[PDB]
Amino acid sequence: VRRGHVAPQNTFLDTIIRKFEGQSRKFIIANARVENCAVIYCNDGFCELCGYSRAEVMQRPCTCDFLHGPRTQRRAAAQIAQALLGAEERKVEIAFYRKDGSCFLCLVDVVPVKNEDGAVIMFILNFEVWTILHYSPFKAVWDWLILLLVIYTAVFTPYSAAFLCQPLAVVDLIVDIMFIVDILINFRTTYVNANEEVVSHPGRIAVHYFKGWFLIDMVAAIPFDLLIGLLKTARLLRLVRVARKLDRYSEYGAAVLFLLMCTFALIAHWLACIWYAIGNMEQPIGWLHNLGDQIGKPYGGPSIKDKYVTALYFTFSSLTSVGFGNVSPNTNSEKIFSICVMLIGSLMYASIFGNVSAIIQRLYSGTARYHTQMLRVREFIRFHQIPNPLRQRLEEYFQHAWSYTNGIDMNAVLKGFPECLQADICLHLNRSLLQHCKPFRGATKGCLRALAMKFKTTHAPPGDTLVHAGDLLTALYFISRGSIEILRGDVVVAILGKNDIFGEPLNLYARPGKSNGDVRALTYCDLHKIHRDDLLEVLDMYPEFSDHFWSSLEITFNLR
Amino acid sequence: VRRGHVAPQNTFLDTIIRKFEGQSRKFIIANARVENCAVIYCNDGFCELCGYSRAEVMQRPCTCDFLHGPRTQRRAAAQIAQALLGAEERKVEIAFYRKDGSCFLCLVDVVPVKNEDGAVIMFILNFEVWTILHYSPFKAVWDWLILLLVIYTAVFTPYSAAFLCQPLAVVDLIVDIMFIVDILINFRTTYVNANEEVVSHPGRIAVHYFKGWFLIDMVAAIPFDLLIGLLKTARLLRLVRVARKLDRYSEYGAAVLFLLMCTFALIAHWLACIWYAIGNMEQPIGWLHNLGDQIGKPYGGPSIKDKYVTALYFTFSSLTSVGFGNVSPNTNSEKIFSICVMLIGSLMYASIFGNVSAIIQRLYSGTARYHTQMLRVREFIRFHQIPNPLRQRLEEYFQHAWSYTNGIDMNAVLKGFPECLQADICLHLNRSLLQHCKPFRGATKGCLRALAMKFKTTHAPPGDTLVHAGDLLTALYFISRGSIEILRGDVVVAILGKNDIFGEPLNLYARPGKSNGDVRALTYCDLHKIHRDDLLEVLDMYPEFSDHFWSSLEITFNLR
Amino acid sequence: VRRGHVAPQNTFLDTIIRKFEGQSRKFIIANARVENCAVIYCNDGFCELCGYSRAEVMQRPCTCDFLHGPRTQRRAAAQIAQALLGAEERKVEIAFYRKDGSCFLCLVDVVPVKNEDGAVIMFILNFEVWTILHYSPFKAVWDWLILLLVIYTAVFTPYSAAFLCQPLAVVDLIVDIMFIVDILINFRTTYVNANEEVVSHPGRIAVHYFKGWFLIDMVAAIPFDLLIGLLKTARLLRLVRVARKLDRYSEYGAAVLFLLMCTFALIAHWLACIWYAIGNMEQPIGWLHNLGDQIGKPYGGPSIKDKYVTALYFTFSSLTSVGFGNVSPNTNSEKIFSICVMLIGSLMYASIFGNVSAIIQRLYSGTARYHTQMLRVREFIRFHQIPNPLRQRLEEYFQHAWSYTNGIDMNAVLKGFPECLQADICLHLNRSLLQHCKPFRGATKGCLRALAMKFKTTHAPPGDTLVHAGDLLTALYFISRGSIEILRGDVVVAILGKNDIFGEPLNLYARPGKSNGDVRALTYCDLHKIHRDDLLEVLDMYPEFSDHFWSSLEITFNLR
């Protein structure tokens, strides 16, 4: 289920501007925490008065020296300066000057705003001539509890209606209380408006709940004493609660299959009850008389245990397209019902199990594409005829890479997000380097995001050659986990464990230098990677970082 | 089935470091085969003692001249040098010096490690102040043998249970032995752990087999003498062996269809037996009495041959959605069973044959996309209205290219793999050139991989013009198979067979030179290709290779 | 159906080299039509003899001046020169010299090859010390005629076998003749070998037809006189002719649906006959007795008209999953058959109509994607809320572009083909320009292909602004059909009809010049397009073409 982000702590500024926008007033806003109180807003009405644009007015003292002129008094201007420090309402009068030259008399209404703590935050200068959340685990698990007792009302209210201290009557009365309790919960609980990402408190929620889904849910919780048994069919409107809250029940993949399969039972259930109703209410030959000849109970009559089973047995067989012929429609009303069940059944059986077949492939989606992606590799091997030592690499790498990634395109997901969140994702992915290592600490946050974007992650399983002898070292690597070894003609030279760096320094050569020897991983080593073209372009942007970077950084193996 | 790569020969170094990591000791490792015994590892504890970082300590003699100072003796340092050559344990004492200046007394524990042959490989200097494989063809074919006799137990154990030197009893006792033998095989056979790519020997396998799939498979192989016929239903747990080993049975495309179709029979089989059980255990009107009136055997009674057939005949018709009405449920228990079979059948018939329909399209996947890809070309021809001489080329090339590649994207597969394995694939693909030809022999392995990446393969069928007269010769070609001819106005000049080269030398012109004449293939000629921009960029990286390349290489046809 | 390209006219050279390759001889080949008889082939055996490589030997006179030395006679060398002009076999002896220095005596066997006309084409110098085609419209339409009379044999041979001047017997004997005629046709007709793209004449075809599909088709055409009616069931093997020739019948989209639907009838047909056979051959209660009670013919017996209908009626209902219950299996054999029909029917009905549902969507594939592509545009309009004057453009352009292209990606098709055939396609697409226009005539074929690749086609419907006033004229246009008008503030200036050019000359400015005014089409104008960056890069390659191009070309509207 969706939950919007909470309103930022500076959103009060928007409501002040939006209220004064309705008044058509002319004003400016200036901050208190800043040194000389720089102006941070100027509406269109203010620019028409003075003549100056936003660019000129913004980032200037709130006393406004440029507005003063010959006609202004020294004593009158001093009253405005003292009013900022004193923190109170003083309507001081003074005659400002425009950009072009003309003067005007104006009333300066200084009204400081304050928070709950008791401190002056902003300066508005007007001119004139018992709570619950919607995303809580309490409500989340209780929605499943509603859905369970909703199924109860879908099953037992038609069976009670059609076929007619008691154990059944007492449990039914407990369900009536839960829906009355549900209405009380829906007032105090929060919701997500389109514009307002979150909303709380009872003054605002009751307006939304009225003129919405309360009218239908109001009828659900109205029991009465006053046969008249048909009034209990209003409890089927409790099923509407599931439709409006469908976003919560569609989260899990397996839970969706339960809904589609249990509804199929309820569809037949109702039709079974409706099929039974057709037999009783026309009784002058039909299907119920016909059943009395099959099972030995002609007319007393057959039992209700049988009467419902045989009726459900029928309507399942009719809408599953079996058609057994133990029971079958003879009268015109029965046949018309069978026509209705065959028509709705052909729509249902096509639509509902078309989804279930898709949901099984959607649940087992990893293993579905895995076999098709595997058959590409097997056809690729048989095409070129690849020998055994390379055969083992392509099979084991593919299964290792797929089991690691779960058959997911990692770069394809990041392209949907913008550069701000892409940087934040990559900042999290490379948290092991940027936090712990020596050179990356002494740097601004813009540099960290800039680097993180160009960084990569490359999982090297046991016995995988990353680089070979005499190769162009494009990359500069960083190791987080595992233990990588460097060799040179079957001679073990290096053993690079955690928090190690290997490659070449970019300052000395200024060219793509050749390698020293091969480098192979022992364990499932987690490591990171960049390029010379990628890295150098970052250091050109940040010159103060570059001198700090290369000095503090220490490569464990210089490769030449 | 997946099989991990064997642990590399230098993995003992990781276990030594990981054991000493638990001790919290401070040490270094140095190689013996190398000249002056360079240090190849240094933990965090060692850097805290001396003060020096990894970059300074690595690639230096293991005697450590930088650690010595004024306080160290000449006789004491000589004991460490002799200990390296002698190969034994000597705890020599000497007072080293730190980087900053301060001294410390320390005990040098030199412990050389040795292999099975009997030679000193490494120097650890501590400081203190009857087998079987899982991927074998024996086990592979025997898993199919298990699956066959598992189907036996799925079919014959319900039929024996429900409907009741003998030929049947003796064959059943042989199957009981095979599962007891299976348990003995599962101990000695290998498996694939998540971390440990391969694992062997009985000390490690028994720990994994216990607390896993042995508990279920233990119950399978427990026969007893002690009617009590229901205890034989535990043999259905032998079916669990197929689920846990499902990765092996899903390899072949046609073999998957056999599983999905034979299970459909077994599903009905069990339900047939369950349908029969419902008739017998309620016998005070039902379906079995009803059958005695159809076939002339009222009550003796009808035969077991019939009794099972009619029961299977029912349950197939019920779950295939036919519903014949020879046999049909009359009692409440029978109807509830029919409701159960209709509900499970609607799920089964939708799910299982949804997969079979996909598996037929997945097996015939080449011919499926071939017709759709063909209809693009036929619509492309009808759109532009292409004449006969060009019509023949597009049809014959498409069918030749598709029959060659089997409708597979060759470049799309390589993009999934990294640059290391991509080079290894391309090294195999261009093995005909790099091994046999004259100039490519005298070169380093980095050059061979660098070239191979930029190379291509272009199959030219009979009568295909590769290059025309007056064209810009971007490429430089190499022929492996077939026989290509060069013409110039219907005059046969060249006949280039195997191991031939044509194009232009890149040293003389330093520009894109024009061609001499046309060039056409006779047979299905296999040849390779590069570009000027691609090739020149490789030779710039390797200057010693470039002078060797152009001198030794000899182009058969210079084209101007 | 696939048909390979005919063997090129110079393929005799390959067979001569391949035959002499078996002999392990050492030789060269030289052309006659060329001036000084340049050598055009040299095997590995020749290079071992002399010492010289291919590069040095190729493109030199066949007399070989470099091979001569001091020991060679003036009179002996003259015999070789006269032998080239005379055209006959002379085994002249002369002692050649190697590259290194050593001499050797050798026999020069000059054997000129000749064609059917009677002219010397090549010079091989050995050294020693009633027809029919497969793709014809005769065979194409006759394969459909076979398939029609194959269906006859599938339908009438079981009906004749199972249920038992005559009109029926005479027509059956005509079909027996057609299959005997088919065998005679299959000898003389051609086929497509994997290596040999085409093959003809009776010496080669009979070897392929034997040990192939003749053995099965031989049994089809063996009638005998000698009840023994079961021998006529061998005529079902005539159905195998359709399977082996399936490539021809899968061409048309609608014709595939006919095969899948007519087979479904034949599947039921056979099963109907098999269902009938079960009734007769067990006759001591069954289904045939049961039918005698429904329709008033107990036992004479019921008619064969009925007996077959009711049997087909059954087997359709069984495998269509209806199950009527007029007729139904009572005996064990009948039920086992119903189990078999339900099992094969569930496989058939899933597989065969899964294809038919796909074939309907594949036949109506244009209209399928059209609606989905339309819904993108309708959602795109509702997203941005586009006004009426632009609304009309996006709707009309999309329908015009889709109706023109039939929903096909034009550039996506060309990427599959190589640069040779891509150029040939684009040469055909821009045939209107390159043939008819003035500047493109005086140019080499390499230039025409180079230009054609970079050219485009842009259909401008009525009232479409191609270029606006003050725009950067990147392109230079060519008009083939229609009539385009140029305006400048609602003033009609130009009327450019067929074979016209507009843009700017690239020689004068050497910069992207601005436009003069707007340009709009009247009719469905067909026109072509290029760019400055695209065009200039071609003219840099061909300097002799560039001076010819700009002088002869004349732009109708210079735009400034």
Image: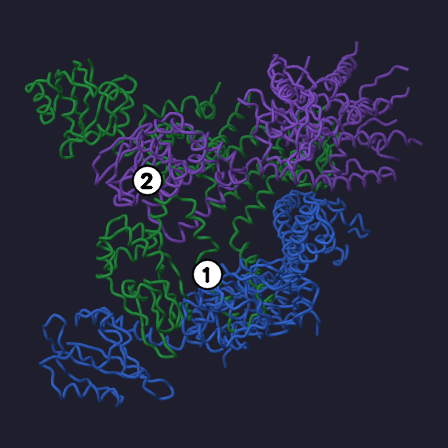
Chain colours: A purple, B green, C blue
Find out whether the residues at labels 1 and 2 contact each other: C-beta distance under 8 Å. Answer: no
Q: Nearer the viewer, residue A548 or A131?
A: A548
> Which residue occupies the extreme front position in the image?
A70
Observer-nearest of C206 and B292: C206
Q: With respect to residue A471, does C555 lie above or below?
A: below
**A105 left or right of C2 in image:** right
Q: Is residue A281 visible?
A: yes
Q: For the residue marked with disc 2, what is the amino acid?
A: Leu
Q: Amino acid at mark 1?
A: Ala
Q: Residues within 10 Å of mark 2 (few under 14, many from 20)?
A: some
Residue C329 location, x and y as percent? 70, 44
Quickly name the residue at label 1. B401
Q: Residue furthest right?
A: A284
Q: Quadrant of the N terminus of chain A?
A: top right
**Mark linked to residue A466:** 2
| Chain of the residue under the numbered disc 2 shown in the image | A
Marks 1/2: CA–CA distance: 35 Å
Q: Secondary structure at mark 1?
A: helix
Identity of the residue drawn at 38% across and 88% down: C117
